[PDB]
Length: 326
Ligand SMILES: Clc1cc(C[NH2+]CCCc2ccccc2)ccc1-c1ccccc1
Image (tube, rainbow, N blue to C red):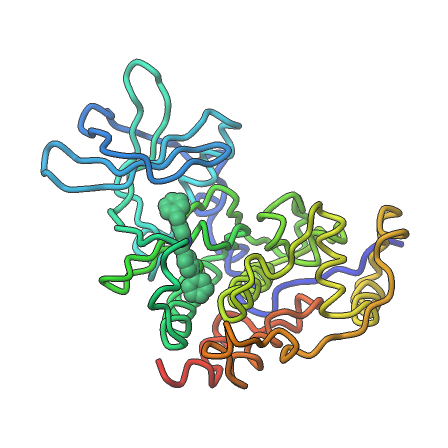
């Protein structure tokens, strides 16, 4: 008959109960100004469909973040802009300040509030058990907020989290893969970055929701507390599920695929194997024990679950004893 339908346990109908204008990005009218008002300072990053810069607004001598969009599908550009406008100002969300276009290139660019990012490959120097809890809570504020606004990020990873450690300022960025959640909609599973893909994407289960972001979050937490980047190190999309199965076990994987009546790809036949469920304590060592606690492990166990419905929602995660200290 096919896979069993599923829907989010929270914010299920938030979009259904709103007007067409809020979620119909294909019909949204994008109006941009002249890029002549901005001068590029330095490169911050580079993506598949973008290049991020530090820039100066010449009319007020204020630093900004400028994201130059590589002309991809116009609906994709429209989706991101609509999403950014809907979320503009939300807690720990990158704030869109302006939309422009260079007169000569006709290339569209997005202008954001300035964030002074501290180096990722040089942040763990003074990043304590408290720091991790504090920044994890800041990400959860962003997540409950965008989820409450009927949006799933679908690309949660360290590269999409900007941290200004001196001011304890965090921003969830790159809303280019984000999408409006509509219950029963079937989404393209070719989202998120390989190491952060939820089991739903890997088993080609299209009816996923907000909980996909909570699996990605769990991946980030595990790499941070265990000092193992990435935590699930797949070499391809099929191998990624094997790496998760080596930790969560194959019994609970079949239990999940049986629950939703998912049919596994033949590519999994020769590689999946048989694996027992491991204890989270197995990943503790001298180099990471100062960041691990029974609270951290309990919180992690409730995020990294095959069953997307069994994972904590962002609002439930904020109530976990791991955050009592913050
Ligand atoms: Cl979420 C995060 C991000 C980081 C650092 N991001 C690097 C972003 C670089 C960049 C890329 C593109 C444009 C602008 C800048 C370091 C640690 C964490 C972290 C904290 C607590 C728990 C787990 C992880």
